[PDB]
Amino acid sequence: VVHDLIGVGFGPSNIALAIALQERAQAQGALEVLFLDKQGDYRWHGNTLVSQSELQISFLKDLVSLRNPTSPYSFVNYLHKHDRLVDFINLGTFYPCRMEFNDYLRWVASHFQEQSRYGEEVLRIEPMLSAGQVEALRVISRNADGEELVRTTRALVVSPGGTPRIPQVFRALKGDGRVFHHSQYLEHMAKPMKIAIIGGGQSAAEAFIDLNDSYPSVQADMILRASALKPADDSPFVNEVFAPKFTDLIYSREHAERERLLREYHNTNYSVVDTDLIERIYGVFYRQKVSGIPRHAFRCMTTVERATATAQGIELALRDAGSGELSVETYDAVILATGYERQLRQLLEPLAEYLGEIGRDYRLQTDERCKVAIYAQGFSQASHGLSDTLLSVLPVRAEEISGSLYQHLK
Ligand SMILES: Cc1cc2nc3c(=O)[nH]c(=O)nc-3n(C[C@H](O)[C@H](O)[C@H](O)COP(=O)(O)OP(=O)(O)OC[C@H]3O[C@@H](n4cnc5c(N)ncnc54)[C@H](O)[C@@H]3O)c2cc1C
Ligand SMILES: N[C@@H](CCCNO)C(=O)O
Image (tube, rainbow, N blue to C red; front, side):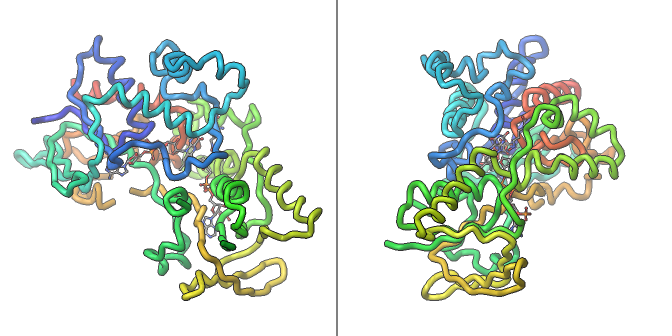
């Protein structure tokens, strides 16, 4: 009945953690562990897996290799197990398609069937009081059939990923199927049509290229408030900001200096597009100048000031900061390629009375009444750096959280 650890989510963060726990098991004893994921059939951002979607990190930053290249869960071992390693080598790329990395993640996760529970959404975590002290946590979940489940645990790891960021102007249109966040792209995309894409980062660029390449009757407008698509910085000195060593460095810094570092290196990860994809998009617009056929529009320096549902489509009032002018365009669909927030608090709401920043070891600081350990993954960019929301340091974070957990449970 009483688990050692329950995890919210079984994406890369918690899969990497399950591996690190398994490595420690022989020397330190196997723990009683469950990871719950709301997806019935696990995919890694499955509704974003368009034909042109390259991984934006080296395959060597897989779930294990930075810690343990001899792990059977390395991307290289995965290829070898699928009789594909020589073929992959002939490709000569560090960047597999995201569809292949999705297959890799599913393959790794399929080794943890005793620990995973799919189709279970965690709704809230409650304190189990015993003589005034929180000795355990109640994890309340709902399965796909709508049944409630209640489980008990000594420790919790919260790794639910981000939530879609919706600009305020589009909030009134929640529930209108014509407006959707890029995270649901494939679900909604599944006859001359006009589609607006809001944003100018990697997701907006991928959405645009997919429309251009696969939906010949779609006229796409990239609507971005910034002046240009700008390239993602992965040059090698800059890229050291993702190294495991940087985690210690940023954590050691005072708050003003942490914020300065994050501002300085913002363009390694946010509001930026892979250089080759920028060149591809620029080429699409350049060819329109050659042909005189303006299928698509690049609306830079443009802000959506109003968005209204009409019988004819979604009407957007567009302010061009270059000219100060307002125009009105109507679209058949609007894709919000506007990224994600990391906040996660109905989940942890019943524990608000006991909470504090996060520790170096990713443990939420609680007052002395709380005897249980709660960890969170992907919510600590402010203190641990730009690797926090990415695949970048997962093998090392997994070793760090798993170490701390054993130390706590000893
Ligand atoms: C489109 C896209 C592309 C990306 N590409 C890259 C890339 O190329 N390289 C890179 O390094 N990073 C990339 N990222 C960053 C991404 O955050 C990480 O790669 C990684 O997915 C984070 O792992 P995670 O397990 O912390 O979160 P997630 O992968 O988001 O997993 C969270 C899991 O929690 C589950 N969940 C959420 N709420 C609940 C609930 N309450 N109960 C139960 N389960 C729940 C979800 O079903 C999900 O499976 C990308 C992100 C996106 C959105
Ligand atoms: N350049 C980073 C990954 C950045 C991913 N951003 O989308 C790294 O090498 O860890």
